Picture 1: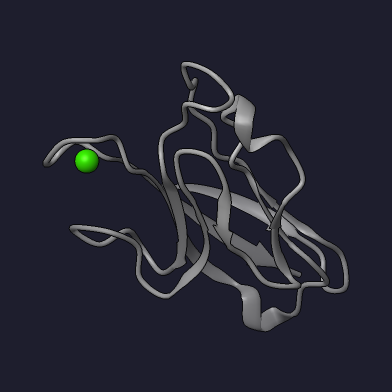
Picture 2: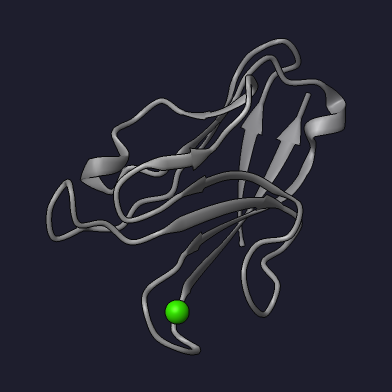
Length: 108
Ligand SMILES: [Ca+2]
């Protein structure tokens, strides 16, 4: 687990990257609130798949290019309620092999 900081009223940046084969040949990724569970993400805030961003909402979005493996999460206009641990999960095809990144956001 690695810790990151943001300020109230600004945007949070939570880095998360992998190296894909090609822009149209990606690995599905999920983000969730809470430490990464055994499988999948809990409390999902964003999802991508082999070609598209399939799930996002007004305050949870990507500022970088997911087709290049930049799956870093932006949380827009944060409040103290956004403090906590987030999971970035790189859902490599196969069993028991995802990359599970735990990110703690501290907000002041
Ligand atoms: Ca897997």
